[PDB]
Image (cartoon, rainbow, N blue to C red):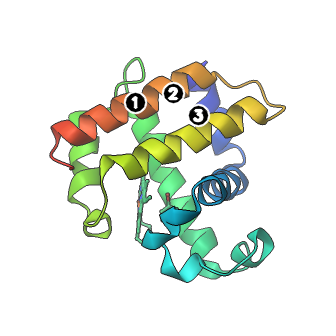
Amino acid sequence: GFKQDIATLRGDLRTYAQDIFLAFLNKYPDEKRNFKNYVGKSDQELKSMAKFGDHTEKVFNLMMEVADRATDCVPLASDASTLVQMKQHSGLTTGNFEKLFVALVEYMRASGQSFDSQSWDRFGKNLVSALSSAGMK
Ligand code: HEM
Ligand SMILES: Oc1ccc(Br)cc1
């Protein structure tokens, strides 16, 4: 289930983080409006850009902690507030997060690994609800 999936992802976190984020960028090319430095690069080129690997891993490091601190796939309000208030998130809306989780769930369903995709769908929806509650537009 959800808790085991956190352990699965954490066991290969940089690889999973990059592959999920790439699936997001490739499913929603317009989302590069928020990632000007990732424009004009193939997947393999992005994986050789230092900030791409380091930032994507740090994003997923924190995402797994938020997932781990959740109860029944509902995140803590403190974690939602932190995600809304981060300076690096100033330009974001909940639709950005909704699309990330759609791509993440699609990736899990297409993988050979045995993920609880429905729980990640709920987690993404509940994170969006918590972000709106904490004041993200
Ligand atoms: C649960 C989901 C997310 C978590 C836990 C998270 C966490 C983080 C963290 C830890 C950083 C700092 C990275 C670093 O400085 O190395 C960061 C930066 C950033 N995040 Fe988020 N993030 C999430 C979702 C998103 C989404 C959906 C978007 C946009 C579609 C986004 C856009 C950005 C941007 C633009 C930055 C700064 C520039 C960059 O690091 O490339 N984040 N995020
Ligand atoms: O550098 C970043 C990588 C992935 C996300 Br999601 C946000 C920022």
User: Mark 3 = which residue?
Assistant: 6
How crowded pointer 3 is (Cα within 10 Å; few <14, some 14-19, many 20+) is rated as some
Kind of residue sitting beneath label 2: Asp
Query: Quadrant for ligand 1?
Result: bottom left
Distance from the alpha carbon under mark 2 to that under mark 1 = 6 Å
Kind of residue sitting beneath label 1: Lys
Location of residue 126 by image quarter: top left
| Residue occupying the point 57% across, 56% down | 28
> Measured from the top left, where is residue 100 in percent x and y?
51, 47
Distance from the alpha carbon under mark 1 to that under mark 3 = 17 Å
Kind of residue sitting beneath label 3: Ile
Q: Are marks 2 and 3 in contact (CB under 8 Å)?
A: no
Location of residue 47 by image quarter: bottom right
User: Would you place residue 66 above or below residue 5 in this image?
Assistant: below
Tally of numbered tags:
3
User: Would you place residue 23 above or below residue 114 in this image?
Assistant: below
